[PDB]
Image (cartoon, rainbow, N blue to C red; front, side, top):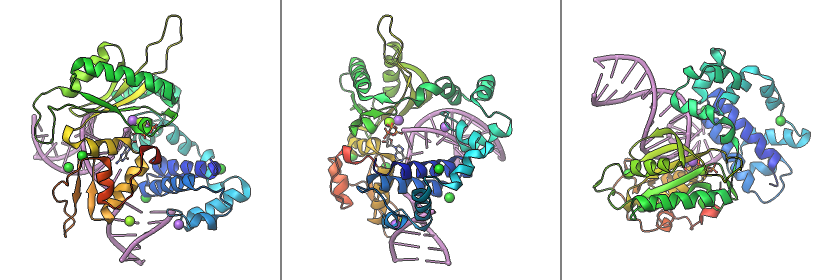
Length: 326
DNA sequence: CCGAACAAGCATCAGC
DNA sequence: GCTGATGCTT
DNA sequence: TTCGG
Ligand SMILES: Nc1nc2c(ncn2[C@H]2C[C@H](O)[C@@H](COP(=O)(O)OP(=O)(O)OP(=O)(O)O)O2)c(=O)[nH]1
Ligand SMILES: [Cl-]
Ligand SMILES: [Cl-]
Ligand SMILES: [Cl-]
Ligand SMILES: [Cl-]
Ligand SMILES: [Mg+2]
Ligand SMILES: [Mg+2]
Ligand code: NA
Ligand code: NA
Ligand code: NA
């Protein structure tokens, strides 16, 4: 972290614009600048130097000059003083509360963790579970714990049906020494882009993980996406592990490579790669890469037999998961 | 200057 | 109930 | 807020 002060400043600005201003393109601009600066292998000495990087424009360069000169950004120092902005920023830290709900809660005089707990009945289910585990969801997951969780998920999935394949993606697959949550890609040969020959494929896996008390709560759940909560089992007399966020995504089996590229991320890596695809005349989602026709309408799915096939289509050299942490 | 900025599943609600 | 927009999230 | 054309 050669430039951690600058990237922290830009992330805090990004969060302000998203959570408070509801200015999504400014949020994306700040996040992209922080990402490209985080990757920059020199200690930045001036905003002019930073402006040479893609995604750093005139306004961010000027803020970097102020930060390098003083160690601080007046704009942030005053955002930190603003009660309304601070409360809105705080409330969005609860899973299920976004910028809109946070401003509405603040309008109704719900502005602190204490306020939220007294007004559980004003929360939807997702927000209620986010509040319940607010502390736990702030903690990182050591990779050793991720390995224990992987072993449970993969073995419990196997006991449901040996033809399931569960793959831990996200930051874990990128080799991170700690993760914010656990992301599991799931396939089964009965579910392809051509047909669903068996129902409840995701449900049965969720049910089994609930049965063994690994999954403890549900935030949202459909046919292909589960968003919920899990917990490692602890030993006798030991303090319990924190509850953890878990996402499971059931992807058509013939579309595994697009799905594993999507679910490995990072989120900014996906945005960059998808934006590059568009400039190359392709569109990429978690299912397919398709060419854009003359009118910009997606054509038919292109053949894909590896993650590298997708990189080849858009004329990118292959990048291993560990080099996608943008 | 100005249009584009990734893509989509699930929960919720408004309107019919 | 269905459809479509919106919020929130990955 | 930044970038490409
Ligand atoms: N195309 C796209 N993909 C996303 C987006 N957000 C997340 N993803 C994909 C890439 C992520 O690596 C993956 C898992 O989402 P997470 O929020 O768990 O991030 P990740 O695991 O990378 O880091 P973390 O969990 O915080 O350690 O989902 C997005 O806004 N767009
Ligand atoms: Cl904006
Ligand atoms: Cl500051
Ligand atoms: Cl694929
Ligand atoms: Cl598709
Ligand atoms: Mg993750
Ligand atoms: Mg562009
Ligand atoms: Na630049
Ligand atoms: Na939130
Ligand atoms: Na996740």
